[PDB]
């Protein structure tokens, strides 16, 4: 009977990843590769 | 920038339909509990959902293998998987190097995203996510990608997912049909866009792609056909009551006109004629005409009959002229016997609320229609349409930068603010940073600091508020009146100053156990100045409790500025300043900042008690546009009453 | 503002009745989960800047909102958005401590929607931002505390919507 | 309550609650069971306390129930016992809350202006609460009544 | 809806003045430029679909996150809606070109654009960028075509940029 | 406020790119007209009270507005109208120097209608008075710069509609 | 612009533009071709100046690119060079407008609060503009370099 | 101290101490021996806390010890250990007082202006107290650690 517990029981943690620089900064990613 | 704002209420478009979403919303629109049908929709889905988890889990894990076997078959001349992010009609294998890296990156990710949306489709249990995202895709992909290569790619994935899974015929067929839908929707060319034609010259024409109206939950459309069994006929009539009265009133209060119900059940009068007679009935008149202004009742009549808000300024102007001429019947007649009504609903179909998902929407009456489609619309008694439409053409109104609600009533005491919830009368206006509000000076018009900044510390001479100053010598300042002198005359003057200083910080005179006795006697001894005394009364825990704590942060800042400086804030620049202090430092520092401001020091010295210096135009209108106090020469032509020449 | 204790008192005061058996049970329910609320508040107090940091990092960073033309491009706007998120987290904590969302009505959601519409702030973007708080909060605060915090943050979302 | 007062003080400085204020709430929460016992005993004999303390009041200050007195008459004595029941109810709210804010907001703020307009001596109402304390302390145990009397003493102190 | 003629009428009607030398000169300036305005409108009517698609393709290469996940041009549904919006801005600029007035651009486009875009979560930055890309696409094509006046083409798109975009400074 | 320069800066900033060739052309066009803009401003600065004087004498003086029963009858009201026309000439110069009517929307026409309706300021008579300024300024400065000034003076008039 | 700040100052005093103020706009419009040349020079090396200033910053302050730093990894270093390019563009707008208000309103007002949330050393970004100034002066003349430096120094001064 | 904080709050309203305020001092004075036990443990093993938490900071954020950082060299590392020793001393003063005022008056008010003039990242100093909390909690009993960490978390909260 205790299978009904979805929102009443323990909530399942969801993995939300950190937002990363995208292909708009491909110019700067190229610059960061040459800055070494 | 735009001078008016209708509001930006949260829009929630349905991106794709699921089985639970399809089941729940079906009875939600009908205003029923989930019956034996809609429960069985879920029951069969929840049982199959366990299997549907096993479909995806295998396909999510082996996702790399499926796309690898696909790309190798389609693309020739090297390895397509170098940079990873059955029936051939007549396809030619595309070269890797010839296609280019940028086009190859698109091609690879789409092949993965096609499979990704297939996995979401099984988990959702409805191929709606496919139908939407695949229907109008053939045309846009044709330009720089071969169609013949895509069909065999999906067909490869169809076989790839079939062989890898292969559990049961009750299990694999779900994978097969959803892939079969996927290829058929991709083979299908882009359908024609839904064209919302303007009903008249006043309203603009719109267009919506055949994809947006494929997911956004279709509004249940009921049509009275004469042959229908009386159960679904009852469902049509209940829906007609749910449209006109916003709710099923026949279930709620047993308020129903059976006289009209009988004629439509037979087919004597059409649904067009039913809506006509029901909206001119005393049942509607009492509820949606009687409690409302002529403008707002018009706005409600729009959503009940046409199923939309008034679209243009000219439309409100036209339909208000109708409701002024013949009233409610004439308004109803104009709404039903329109070119729009007979185009949408015709004669048989019950009117339905056409919102964000149903049709293409115009960027004019967005937030005005959003609040109208809500069930909290017949409580907003302030018109939202005619107000915004008129404010659109006009410049920025006399208003606080953070809305009309942020403005307190210009009264002696009590911070009274218009509530957002209680009687919706929110009037947003796009105010920018460097926007100074025009304020009317209490004293001389020449003594305004906007035009005369030198005359900021000039006292209003029987034009504005009375100025309280510690000009006279405080009692027991010098040791001239030694020991005695019981009748020291300069004692009542400083006590009247204290009371006025209390009256400025707190609009009203305080009680016995509220007066700060420590601060009073320090001023009376001459230990602290008036500037420090005003600061201490505003730094009091009572001022925190009475004006700061129960009110909205920026409402509390605005009222404090109207009490300590006797002036509303000019705009954003000042409001943002004190709001920044309120966030970091707190309430006490906001008090400190308003007292230690240069403008405070210029207007009021160390001995000067603050006073009302500037009013809002709306505030002065409340004071001097009543029956009394209003002069004869304000907004009236004055004729010189002279005795006639025969007299 | 009123808390869970004050809500019981004010309900008894308006009727003019002494605290009855049902009222005593309502208070005991709050006193059952009170140590949990205090411990929950101390976690948020420590990670005040940290929760806001990750919330922006998971939703708002490297988006069209923070990009030029957006409503969170300029540093003055970015700081103003951070300021708002600092307000939302603090007042949610107060409401969590109180056990009542009456403070959120009085202080926050009295004229927030009218302010945001006048400013031209995307409410859709803020709802996503406060939803981003909800996950980061529950990661540090716990499950039962995360459920409590999850309600009041959704109430801020509900008021804005 | 004490939760409300702490939050308002915290919002005044625009900061999260100090661990001193956090320790204030948690100890009140754990020591709330004793506070509910006080409220139950005061409610249990609410018609016993008011009646006894009223009798103590009209013996100590009989000029109140003499011609010229504010509570002179069968109707006016009844209104006085009605007033005494209000303050006893206010005490029960105060003990439960762990703060004197609910007593202040309802039945202490603007009490001086109220009893002035009615023509009631404020020192006599302070005496009625003082006698109300004595009857209540007799019913409750030593340590339990001692922390309960502090809420009575505020009502005395604010009026007298 | 108001054109350059109606705006000038409304300006002189407000004051209650007859059309003077300054009024007649402004009308004459419209009527002489009118031939170029229709010819510019004939150009964009010819290349309505081609410009919209190419300007979008430039926009999603400038800001790639739009057509990437969490972007508001990711799905086909969103892609069709964005190209529809790009079609709208070109269509109402088409009206604004002949009208020589930005009232049509204000009334039916800009008035409730910020409220809508903030509701669904549609970006306002990449939008005005996409409008400005269209502007550069028209101007270059108008420079290629045999057109004497091309300066009026920049006017509606810049007004679309000014009104919709956030006040940075 | 926004001038012609900051309008180009604003447009470039929200795009998130450097000032292109088209942006440079818009600046150079303003700097070419800037010589005429400063010249006109200096003459209006020196002849400030005289323009107002001529405008009041043209429209307002010896009328029903200045006579008893009128709104420009009282001395505190007369000096207010002088100051009002002192505002209009000053801010029109400001907008003329700027090259944009942004300042007029932010300071001048920012709830001006509701101000004038509350006090009982004649809307028709004030518009004619601004037109009286417009005619005097154009005759004093020139046919090019006075017409350029007349655009912003008509903007105030059309804002009072 | 130098116009906007002149207007604001004149509006605050409620007066027309000073003969001194009008002469500064006169000197601005005549030297409008000169300041647009500096902008084109800065635009010309939009990927060269910030590149050189980047390399010079990461050798002077290697803790930035070291583990535990704010700009650790190729993704975060890209964001640092993005900030470099933003501020260089902000100076480019500044030299064109001849004012610090088109600079401050974008990326100086509330910048300490801005970088605090990201956990960025503000004094390191102050050194970022310092290195930008030195490279920009290198790829420029002498007389126009001092005019460019003045607006660069404001960006340094308000940040540090 | 919690006594002083009570007095100044009562003096601001010009009133005697609240029944709750007097009870809190009573609860503090009874648990004063427990607060002394927290101090005696932290003072006894003071050098072991700061050394471990210091090293735990240096492994987490090595950019501090790396060149370009604030605490570069053995002398500057010893200064960072001293800074943490000073802050551990503030916590011990905080727990005996029962209030965060002693911590505020010495080493919290105007700390952001201080470490700016030193060029020290304040978020790294915030993380050092986080590590100091972790080692101290593992040193002494959990019932005393929960009380100790409450004052530690305030130092973290005000720092970050
Ligand atoms: C005449 C005394 C003054 C005056 C009136 C005026 N009114 C309008 C237009 C509208 N009138 C209303 C008001 C009402 N709606 C209601 O529900 C009621 C109560 C039953 C009333 C009286 C509204 C909403 C409108 C808008 C409809 C429309 O566009 O006509 C105007 C026209 C203004 C315009 O063209 O925008 C006028 C002039 N104003 C004056 O000048 C007189 C002193
Ligand atoms: C008594 C006849 C009835 C009554 C009164 C009542 N008033 C308040 C509180 C306020 N009274 C006002 C109103 C005014 N503001 C003004 O400027 C003037 C004219 C000079 C008046 C009369 C205001 C602003 C308030 C708000 C708080 C304040 O005092 O500033 C209350 C308390 C309401 C509350 O809940 O706070 C009451 C009860 N109500 C009755 O029951 C009587 C019939
Ligand atoms: C951050 C999640 C998003 C965002 C926020 C944002 N808001 C504003 C503007 C304001 N916010 C408020 C609102 C409040 N008033 C109150 O009383 C409280 C506390 C309960 C709040 C939260 C106010 C008053 C302002 C105006 C301040 C000002 O004058 O600057 C901005 C600033 C926008 C601008 O400068 O025009 C921002 C950035 N918007 C986003 O883009 C984020 C997704
Ligand atoms: C050709 C062999 C392959 C191919 C190439 C290709 N793709 C794009 C870009 C897009 N892909 C899509 C499609 C989708 N949108 C959805 O909702 C889904 C899930 C059902 C998919 C797969 C869209 C809309 C685009 C445009 C957005 C973008 O830029 O990414 C291109 C670029 C188009 C152009 O020339 O402008 C190309 C060349 N895609 C295929 O279908 C083949 C596997
Ligand atoms: C493309 C340039 C960008 C983009 C577009 C986009 N818009 C929506 C949503 C809507 N667009 C409008 C706006 C208008 N309708 C009008 O009448 C006018 C004036 C002519 C405009 C500009 C409206 C009303 C909607 C909502 C309903 C509808 O589609 O008609 C979407 C859909 C968002 C969703 O996912 O639901 C999109 C994608 N988005 C981008 O990212 C581009 C920068
Ligand atoms: C005579 C003593 C001096 C003098 C008079 C003079 N006045 C004007 C112009 C005006 N005077 C007023 C002043 C008032 N009218 C009022 O309503 C009141 C308050 C009751 C006063 C004091 C006004 C408003 C006018 C304008 C006239 C009109 O109605 O239009 C003039 C004419 C100025 C001109 O050349 O236009 C004159 C000559 N001048 C002197 O030299 C005497 C010392
Ligand atoms: C003269 C053209 C007409 C006229 C004017 C008149 N105005 C007032 C009073 C005020 N004028 C304003 C308006 C402004 N203040 C600002 O900040 C701005 C924007 C730059 C303006 C234009 C204000 C605020 C007032 C109120 C007083 C004050 O200065 O604070 C009056 C007096 C009204 C009264 O009865 O007090 C008058 C007469 N009216 C006419 O008759 C002319 C046609
Ligand atoms: C390089 C000098 C230093 C550095 C940079 C760095 N910055 C971020 C994050 C952001 N940078 C900004 C700042 C701006 N945006 C603007 O609008 C302006 C004014 C024109 C500037 C300068 C913002 C808003 C962000 C957020 C990212 C985004 O907008 O998408 C990071 C990333 C850190 C993180 O992930 O939290 C970095 C690394 N860091 C250093 O250590 C250098 C000394």
Image (cartoon, coloured by chain):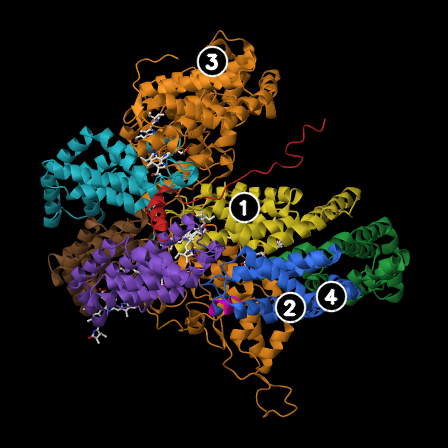
Chain colours: A red, B orange, C yellow, D green, E cyan, F brown, G purple, H blue
Label 3 to label 4: alpha-carbon separation: 73 Å
Disc 4, SS: helix
Which residue matches tag 3? B224
- Pointer 4 and pointer 1 on the same chain: no
**Does residue H116 belong to the magenta stretch?**
yes
Disc 3, SS: loop
CB contact under 8 Å: marks 3 and 4: no
Q: Give the residues in magenta.
A: H111-117
Label 2 to label 3: alpha-carbon separation: 80 Å
| Local crowd size for mark 2, using a 10 Å CA cut-off: few (<14), some (14–19), many (≥20) | many
- Pointer 4 and pointer 2 on the same chain: no
| Local crowd size for mark 4, using a 10 Å CA cut-off: few (<14), some (14–19), many (≥20) | some
Quadrant holding the C terminus of chain B: bottom left
Question: What is the chain letter for disc 2?
Answer: H
Q: Identify the mark at residue H90; answer none if there is no mark.
A: 2
- Pointer 3 and pointer 1 on the same chain: no
């Amino acid at each position: 009977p205790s299978q009904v517990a979805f929102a009443s029981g323990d909530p399942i943690p969801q993995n939300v990843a950190r937002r990363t620089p995208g292909p708009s900064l491909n110019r700067f990613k190229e610059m960061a590769r040459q800055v070494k | 920038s735009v001078k008016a704002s209708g509001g930006s209420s949260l829009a929630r478009p349905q991106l794709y339909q699921t089985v639970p979403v399809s089941a729940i919303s079906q009875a939600e629109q009908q205003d029923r509990f989930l019956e034996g049908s809609e429960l069985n929709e879920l029951t069969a889905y929840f049982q199959s959902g366990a299997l549907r988890l096993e479909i995806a889990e295998t396909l999510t894990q082996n996702a790399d293998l499926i796309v690898s076997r696909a790309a190798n078959r389609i693309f020739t001349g090297g390895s397509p998987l170098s940079y990873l992010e059955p029936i051939p009609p007549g396809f030619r294998p595309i070269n890797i190097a010839r296609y280019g890296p940028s086009n190859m990156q698109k091609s690879l990710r789409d092949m993965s995203w096609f499979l990704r949306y297939t996995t979401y489709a099984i988990v959702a249990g409805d191929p709606n996510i496919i139908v939407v995202n695949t229907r109008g895709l053939k045309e846009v992909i044709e330009n720089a990608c071969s169609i013949d290569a895509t069909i065999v790619a999906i067909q490869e994935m169809r076989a790839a997912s079939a062989d890898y899974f292969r559990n049961n015929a009750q299990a694999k067929e779900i994978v097969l049909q959803y892939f079969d839908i996927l290829l058929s929707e991709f083979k299908a060319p882009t359908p024609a866009n839904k064209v919302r034609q303007g009903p008249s010259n006043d309203i603009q024409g719109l267009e919506l792609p055949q994809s947006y109206f494929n997911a956004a939950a279709k509004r249940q459309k009921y049509a009275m056909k004469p042959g229908l069994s009386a159960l679904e006929k009852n469902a049509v009539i209940k829906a007609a009551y749910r449209q006109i009265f916003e709710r099923d009133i026949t279930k709620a209060y047993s308020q129903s006109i059976s006289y009209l119900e009988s004629q439509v059940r037979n087919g004597d009068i059409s649904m067009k004629e039913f809506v006509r007679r029901l909206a001119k009935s005393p049942l509607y008149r009492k509820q949606f005409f009687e409690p409302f202004i002529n403008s707002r009742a018009l706005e409600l009549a729009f959503r009940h009959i046409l199923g939309r808000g008034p679209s243009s300024r000219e439309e409100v102007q036209k339909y208000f002229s109708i409701v002024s001429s013949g009233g409610l019947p004439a308004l109803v007649d104009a709404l039903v016997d329109s070119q729009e009504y007979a185009d949408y609903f015709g004669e048989e179909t019950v009117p339905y609320l056409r919102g964000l998902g149903v049709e293409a929407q115009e960027c004019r009456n967005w937030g005005m229609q959003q609040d109208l489609f809500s069930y909290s619309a017949p409580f907003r008694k302030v018109p939202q349409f005619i107000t915004t439409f008129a404010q659109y053409d006009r410049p920025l109104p006399d208003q606080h930068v953070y809305g009309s609600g942020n403005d307190p009533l210009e009264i002696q005491f009590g911070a009274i603010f218009p509530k957002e919830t209680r009687n919706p009368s929110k009037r947003p206006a796009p105010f920018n940073k460097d926007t100074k509000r025009i304020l009317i000076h209490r004293g001389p018009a020449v003594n305004n600091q906007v035009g005369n900044p030198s005359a900021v510390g000039e006292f209003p001479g029987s034009l504005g508020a009375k100025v309280f100053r510690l000009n006279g010598g405080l009692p027991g300042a010098k040791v001239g009146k030694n020991t005695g002198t019981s009748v020291k005359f300069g004692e009542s003057s400083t006590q009247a100053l204290i009371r006025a200083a209390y009256r400025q910080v707190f609009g009203r005179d305080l009680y016995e156990g509220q007066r700060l006795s420590v601060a009073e006697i320090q001023l009376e001894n001459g230990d602290i100045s008036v500037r420090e005394f005003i600061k201490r009364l505003a730094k009091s825990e009572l001022f925190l409790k009475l004006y700061w704590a129960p009110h909205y942060v920026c409402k509390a800042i605005e009222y404090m500025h109207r009490r300590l400086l006797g002036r509303p804030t000019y705009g954003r620049q000042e409001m943002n300043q004190y709001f920044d202090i309120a966030s970091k430092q707190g309430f006490y520092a906001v008090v400190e900042a308003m007292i230690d401001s240069k403008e405070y020091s210029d207007a009021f010295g160390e001995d000067t008690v603050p006073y009302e210096r500037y009013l809002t135009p709306g505030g002065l209108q409340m004071r001097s546009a009543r029956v009394g106090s209003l002069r004869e020469d304000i907004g009236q032509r004055v004729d010189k009453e002279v005795t006639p020449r025969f007299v | 503002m009123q808390d869970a204790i004050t809500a019981v008192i004010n309900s008894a005061d308006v009727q003019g009745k002494y605290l009855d058996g049902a009222a005593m049970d309502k208070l005991k329910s709050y006193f059952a989960s009170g140590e949990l609320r205090v411990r929950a508040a101390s976690v948020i107090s420590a990670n005040a800047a940290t929760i806001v940091k990750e919330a922006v990092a998971k939703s708002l960073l490297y988006s069209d909102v923070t990009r030029p033309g957006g409503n969170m491009y300029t540093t003055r706007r970015y700081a103003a958005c951070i300021r708002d998120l600092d307000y939302y987290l603090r007042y949610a904590t107060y409401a969590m401590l109180a056990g009542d969302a009456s403070i959120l009505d009085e202080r926050v959601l009295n004229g927030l929607k009218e302010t945001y519409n006048s400013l031209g702030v995307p409410i859709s973007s803020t709802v996503q931002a406060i939803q981003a708080i909800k996950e980061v909060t529950a990661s540090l605060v716990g499950a039962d505390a995360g459920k409590e915090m999850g309600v009041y943050l959704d109430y801020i979302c509900s008021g804005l919507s | 309550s004490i939760v409300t007062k702490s939050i308002v003080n915290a919002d005044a400085e625009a900061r999260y609650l100090s661990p001193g204020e956090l320790d204030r709430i948690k100890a009140f929460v754990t020591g709330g069971a004793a506070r509910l016992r006080i409220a139950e005993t005061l409610t249990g004999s609410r018609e016993t306390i008011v009646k006894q303390a009223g009798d103590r009041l009209f013996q100590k200050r009989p000029d109140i129930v003499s011609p010229g007195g504010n509570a002179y008459g069968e109707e006016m004595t009844a209104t006085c016992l009605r007033d005494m029941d209000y303050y006893l109810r206010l005490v029960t709210y105060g003990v439960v809350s762990g703060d004197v804010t609910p007593i202040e907001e309802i039945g202490l703020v603007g009490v001086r202006e109220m009893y002035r307009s009615l023509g009631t001596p404020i020192e006599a109402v302070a005496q009625s609460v003082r006698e109300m304390k004595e009857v209540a302390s007799g019913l409750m145990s030593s340590d339990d009544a001692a922390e309960a009397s502090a809420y009575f003493d505020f009502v005395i102190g604010k009026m007298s | 809806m108001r054109d350059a003629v109606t705006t000038l009428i409304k300006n002189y009607d407000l004051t209650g003045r007859y059309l003077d030398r300054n009024a007649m000169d402004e009308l004459k300036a419209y009527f002489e430029s009118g031939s170029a305005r229709i010819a510019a409108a004939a150009m964009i009517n010819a290349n309505s679909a081609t410009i919209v698609k190419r300007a979008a393709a430039q926009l999603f290469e400038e800001i790639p996150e739009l057509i990437r996940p969490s972007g508001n041009a990711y799905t086909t549904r969103r892609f069709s809606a964005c190209l529809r919006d790009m079609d709208y801005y070109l269509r109402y600029a088409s009206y604004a070109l002949i009208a020589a007035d930005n009232n049509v651009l204000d009334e039916r486009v800009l008035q409730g654009l910020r409220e809508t875009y903030n509701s669904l979560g549609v970006p306002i930055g990449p939008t005005v960028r996409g409008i400005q890309i269209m502007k550069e696409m028209i101007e270059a094509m108008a420079e290629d075509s045999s057109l004497n006046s091309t300066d009026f083409i920049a006017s509606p798109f810049d007004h679309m940029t000014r009104e919709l975009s956030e006040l940075s400074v």
